[PDB]
Image (spheres, coloured by chain):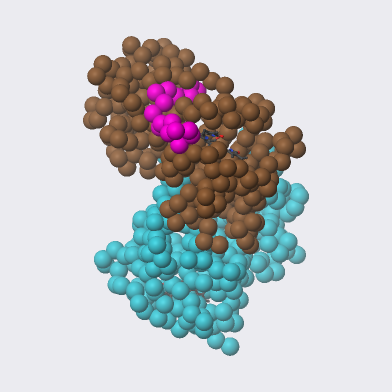
Chain colours: A brown, B cyan
């Protein structure tokens, strides 16, 4: 048994700082809604399950949202602009929608505290970041550039490159840190700290974020006949394995984010980030800029 | 003599669809203004020369603009938001500012016809583009990906990869085209079609755009004692060599854009684009996304 066996892709629950919905196609009837919807959205699961999405959307953004949701080109279209009209009182969300195993999953995170131009911060992050990565003259300089850039953009206490060896053991080959975070640079860890089914999932889904390791999972409720494990492999809000939360607690880490580094189709390593005290809800534009930099680094892993 | 000798970096004039200003430091007094300022800005050179920039800027965007102009971090801060208050009647511009040879040059192009979210189109362009470039499995697939993406983003009739050989002759090794543009794929051209001082300039300044080859150059006027050739090497609006305009006329090309491809610090090739009929004022976000893709391709020129 041991670590390789837990089915981390179907926990039945999400991290409660966003809301997860499942939408029928083509009608966009909600078949599933996470149970934190009252706190986040201002509606109960009973109001949600079996209602059409449009009923809750401010009418002027409604048709474009529905058009996007039916597009597949789906992302490419993320993030979706979601204005949730309840009281109302519009609430604003970035929607991240994806299709997996026959389900259309729409995840809602509250739109950033504004106020700077939308997507300007992404524009600058990836331009400045690309040119620092291109200054690197070898693999070690690349790693140190990436970790400095990611720590700069996010404000995480620690950011490392964690490289896998042939046996899937890993080592900390680059680190940028606040002084206040103990230095992990140079440490090697056994393969079971990132077990096989996690590594397999992380070859497909290149980003995970845990803005606080102390949260109450919000169960995903479903219409009768629906529900039945929801495959959450590509869902950003997926509740993470409790044994990993305990590992982070024991490391003394309150919040985490990691990004897969790919090479020739195979997981090569991770950019891994920790907040040592306090939480870390990384804004959408920052997270996405960091993933973009990880894709650039992955493409450069030919030098 | 021949082609290598013309001093293309100091033509004394600009392409008239934007305005070029030179600003003193730290006071931001205009020492130079291109003579098309009446058409573009609504002020004469006489009103401009020796006035402080702030006098013309809408007061609520004035302090941040001046702060940026004095920053160096200068870009990194481009584009600058420039609201020009004359009549007034605000007019809106993207400012591209740079320092070169001791001058602070501010170039003003009219802000795009709006209306979509600012920088959203850049966000999508570089994300979708990066993932198509990463699908390429060899140099030829890379070239064909780049040319398809750039043509898709811009709408140019033709987009090619033009690769330099050891003697600086070039060949068209990839092409995407409207059918209506003759195919240049496979053609080789002599080194003098892109002469030595152009190639040297294009190792430093990675983008040039000619939205119409038929334009009246707008001379750059200067305060007494100033003026004296303005080095326009890094200026986007720099008027281009008339012999090159004739070459484009003769190719049957009405508008052009090219991007340098760099490898190990040396010019490797160009992404070159043509509009065969009609003009092509590529919006700022599109141009900048194309340059970003050229930087990615340049970084990948290790495979
Ligand atoms: C057998 C069970 C497990 C033991 C024992 C253990 O130590 N982890 C077990 C299961 C497990 N881990 C993860 C995900 C995971 N683990 C890491 C490990 C590290 N983070 C670091 O910074 C370092 C070294 C400094 C190590 C080593 C990481 C980065 C991750 C990814 C998640 C994150 O970024 O925090 C999982 C999967 C958790 C999930 O996706 O649900 C499991 C089951
Ligand atoms: C000796 C004078 C010149 C002769 C003869 C000639 O043919 N060109 C001469 C000078 C010259 N060229 C350029 C810039 C330039 N030339 C090219 C050439 C090509 N564009 C194509 O698509 C192809 C093949 C299909 C060729 C070959 C290009 C791309 C450029 C860059 C400008 C642009 O993108 O249109 C200059 C410099 C012009 C300037 O920067 O002021 C000069 C002096």
The residue under the point 39% across, 60% down is B136
The residue under the point 75% across, 65% down is B225
Magenta segment main secondary structure = loop
The residue under the point 67% across, 36% down is A157
Does the magenta run of residues contain B291? no
How far across and down, in percent of the image, does residue A98 sit?
Answer: 36, 35
| Rendering quarter of residue B5 | bottom right
Looking at the rendered structure, the number of numbered marks drawn on it comes to 0
Does the magenta run of residues contain A11? yes
How far across and down, in percent of the image, does residue B269 sit?
Answer: 49, 71
Residue B302 vertical placement versus B243 (above, below): above
Quarter holding the N terminus of chain A is: top left
The residue under the point 32% across, 36% down is A100
Q: Is residue B110 visible?
A: no
Quarter holding the C terminus of chain A is: bottom right
Frontmost residue, A283 versus B188: A283
Magenta part of the chain: A1-18
Position of residue B17 in the picture relative to residue A128 (left or right): left
How far across and down, in percent of the image, does residue B189 sit?
Answer: 42, 81
Residue A224 vertical placement versus A108 (above, below): above
Residue B155 vertical placement versus B215 (above, below): above
Frontmost residue, B263 versus A83: B263
Position of residue B182 in the picture relative to residue B36 (left or right): left
| Rendering quarter of residue A189 | top right
Residue farthest to the bottom? Answer: B1
How far across and down, in percent of the image, does residue B79 sit?
Answer: 57, 48
Frontmost residue, A99 versus B292: A99
Q: Is residue A144 visible?
A: yes
Position of residue B3 in the picture relative to residue A56 (left or right): right
């Amino acid at each position: 048994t041991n670590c390789d066996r837990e089915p981390i892709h179907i926990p039945g629950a999400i991290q409660p700082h966003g809301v997860l919905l499942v939408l029928s196609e083509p009608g966009l009837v909600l078949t599933h809604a996470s149970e934190n919807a009252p706190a986040v959205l201002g509606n109960s699961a009973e109001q949600l399950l079996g209602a059409p999405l449009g009923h809750f959307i401010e009418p002027s953004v409604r048709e474009p949202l529905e058009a996007d949701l039916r597009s597949a080109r789906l992302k490419q279209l993320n993030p979706l602009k979601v204005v949730w009209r309840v009281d109302g009182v519009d609430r604003f969300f970035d929607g991240i929608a994806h299709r997996h195993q026959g389900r259309l999953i729409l995840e809602l995170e509250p739109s950033s505290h504004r106020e700077a131009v939308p997507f300007l911060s992404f524009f600058h992050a990836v331009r400045d970041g690309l040119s620092r990565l291109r200054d690197a003259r070898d693999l070690q300089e690349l790693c140190e550039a990436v970790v400095q850039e990611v720590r700069g953009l996010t404000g995480f206490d620690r950011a490392i490159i964690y490289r896998f060896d042939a046996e899937w053991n890993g080592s900390v080959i680059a680190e940028a840190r606040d002084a206040r975070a103990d230095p992990y640079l140079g440490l090697h860890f056994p393969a079971s700290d990132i077990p096989r089914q996690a590594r397999e999932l992380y070859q497909l889904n290149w980003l995970r974020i845990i803005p606080t390791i102390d949260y109450q999972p919000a169960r995903v409720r479903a219409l009768p006949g629906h529900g039945e494990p929801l495959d959450l492999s590509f869902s950003v809000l997926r509740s993470v394995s409790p044994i990993h939360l305990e590992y982070l607690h024991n490391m003394g880490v309150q919040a985490s984010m990691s990004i897969s580094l790919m090479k020739d189709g195979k997981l090569w390593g991770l950019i891994s980030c920790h907040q040592v005290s306090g939480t870390r809800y990384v804004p959408y534009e920052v997270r996405t800029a960091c993933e973009f930099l990880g894709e650039v680094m992955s493409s450069l892993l030919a030098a």
